[PDB]
Image (tube, rainbow, N blue to C red; front, side):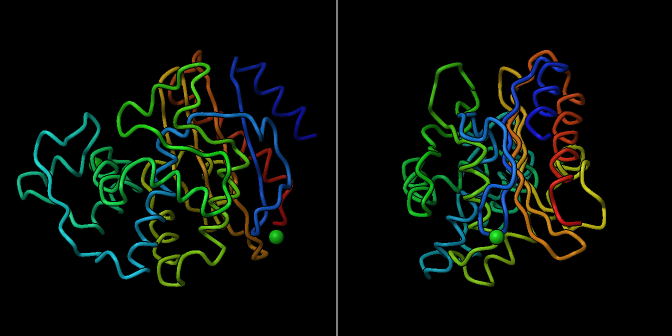
Amino acid sequence: DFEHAISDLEAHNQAKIGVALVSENGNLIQGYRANERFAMCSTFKLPLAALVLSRIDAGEENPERKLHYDSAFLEEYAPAAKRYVATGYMTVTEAIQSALQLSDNAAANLLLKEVGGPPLLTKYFRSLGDKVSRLDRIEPTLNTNTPGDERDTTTPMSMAQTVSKLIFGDTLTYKSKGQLRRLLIGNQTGDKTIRAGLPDSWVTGDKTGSCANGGRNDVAFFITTAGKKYVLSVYTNAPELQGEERALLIASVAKLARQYVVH
Ligand SMILES: [Cl-]
Ligand SMILES: [Cl-]
């Protein structure tokens, strides 16, 4: 069964694995360490983008607005922001696309600045009914993944439920929900993680993250050939594995989890 299979992956890979598979409406189908805390790492960028889209939905933000910055605002991993910095800005839309599909840390920090900072993202989690997830730091220090530190954490179940609400629920408008979905489908960093453990006929979108201390995470939505809709969150700490092995572990989790979905 699912619990025993995940436990077996833990033992074999010297890893801690947290996973939740939920239905379209956020109801738990299978989980393992589903209520234990893990660092969000870059998975926070999905609900961050949704918050910015909610501001656009509210008429408070313009997708073409220029978010200005200079070289001091750059981060070590900021492939898009490094290209645009000479112009002095990225638009809201460019920053959303870059933060989600490239995981650009300067674009994420631009958006954190746009929404009012980590406390305002935490408020948004609470507004959605997520009682657990919390952002405390900006990039890059949110990635420290320090044992016993609750800063910048979620649980697999809380993140799965929150993403199900954003992707399949009605908090965003139909326009913004569709935009978020198409952006996640075009994610460029997830080809070897959850998506690699799902049939290529299924529509899938995802947001990955990596952290210190061997953290490697991925949260995906997918729609099967039967038209059934799911969210899968996978949080791992696997300090004894190499990068490619960490992705394979997450793919393996997804293969186990898909034994419980209607194909
Ligand atoms: Cl459901
Ligand atoms: Cl790039």
